[PDB]
Every structure is written in C-alpha cells, then in structure tokens.
Image (cartoon, rainbow, N blue to C red):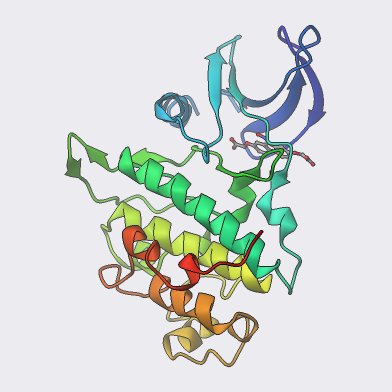
Length: 263
Ligand SMILES: O=C(O)COc1ccc2c(c1)C(=NO)c1cc(OCC(=O)O)ccc1-2
C-alpha cells in the first residue's frame, strides 16, 4: 500500500513490523520496515542515518525512507533466505562447512561496519538474514551507534543487545570498547551454529554454565559437540578480559578459519 503492495507480514517486532512488498508493475520485492513514531522519533532518526552510510555485500541494502504521517517506512533489501536462526537445528547445529561460510561472511560484514566506525551492538542469528544464494547479511541497525568519528574512538556506556549474546564487560564496566563486544557476540553465534544451543543465559559469575567455561570444563556441552579446531577459536574469542580477547585481523589468521571444508 504505497506505489508497492504489502503481501505478507515478515518480522513482527516491538515498534512495528517488516513486510514483504512487491511492486505490481515491475514485480520487484522489498522488505518494508514500518515504524509508527507514536507507538520513538530519536532512535529511528539514527537507524536511517546509519543505514544511509552502509554499502557492502554482507549488510542488508538500504533503498530509502518516506514519512507518510506518523509512519516511517524503511525500504530494505528483502532476503529470501530468511534468518540464519532458522538454519540452526536445536541441539545439533549445522554442518561445519556451512558454519564456516556464514562465519566468513559475518566477519566480512563486521570488518566493514567497524572500518566505518559503526558497531551493530546486537549480532545474533535472528539478525542475520540470508539472501537467494544463501549469502549472509547483517540486519537491523536499530541499536547501532558510532564509536569512531574523525579517527577518535569513544567508549560506549549504554548497555544493549541480547543477554546470551552480550559480552561480560558490558555487564561489569561503566565504559567499554565497542569492537570486542561485537567480536564476543560473533563467537556466541559460532557456538550457536556448531552445537545448536547457547552456552549460558548471560556471562555472569552468577551463571553456572559461564563459570564452567572460564574453568575450561569443555567436557560439558555445548562444547563437547564442537571439535577441537573451531573450539580452539572459541577459546580465543570468548576470553573475559576484553583486552586479551582476539581481534578480527587475528581471527582471520586462526587455523580453523583458514581450513578448507566446503565445495
Ligand atoms: O523466506 C522466508 O521464509 C521469509 O524471508 C524473510 C523473513 C524475515 C525477514 C526477511 C525475509 C527480511 N528481509 O529483509 C527481514 C528483514 C527484517 O528486518 C528487521 C529490522 O530491520 O529490524 C526482519 C525480518 C526479515
């Protein structure tokens, strides 16, 4: 209903929905995200402003914005693959070779964002959309924010994202660096793909399962399901002191990351 028709509901979140929109002339498809500024106008001015900076093969394409009353419409690549969340078999995961591919692509996407000084802040499988040839695209810049401007980094102080994905320091410190938290959530997504389960509800000393990982009890799952090469990488990503935690340029030199698996 706006030059294009709204065919089916797609991602009914809080604040609005995402629809599938076909143009009836050209037959082309898009995702219309629909935010009713009555049911924030501030976090939404940022989303689109961030979205206009973005252009990469692993980040959902931004086509434009119209205001139509209270109603903001963001015109967004439609990913006919859907969510990576759905290619994770509960308790089992997915073939190592697909995980490694999705991880290569997620890395590419994140390097990109980080190189333009943007942290996504909410990387989880629900936010990783797949296109028609199963290429992974980083989605939903609703919580994204700028952490380098004019070549100066600034620490974040707002807590956000999704607890099982979040990095311990975001719980513990008043200010933290933006990049390592994005790395940590990327690691949790790896664990998710390779084991089909989340290792803990939040990285708290108060959280049993989290305490067992710091004690290297990798004899429990989801670790036992994982396999020594990728698990060695997870050991370098899910490090607690954000400063000792591996960085992306170094993930790119890790053995499992550079292992041939897939045709
Ligand atoms: O193939 C299917 O079964 C459905 O395909 C989908 C399913 C969910 C979503 C899409 C495509 C999207 N394409 O862009 C999409 C975008 C979304 O954006 C959310 C945001 O920007 O917050 C959310 C859900 C979906």
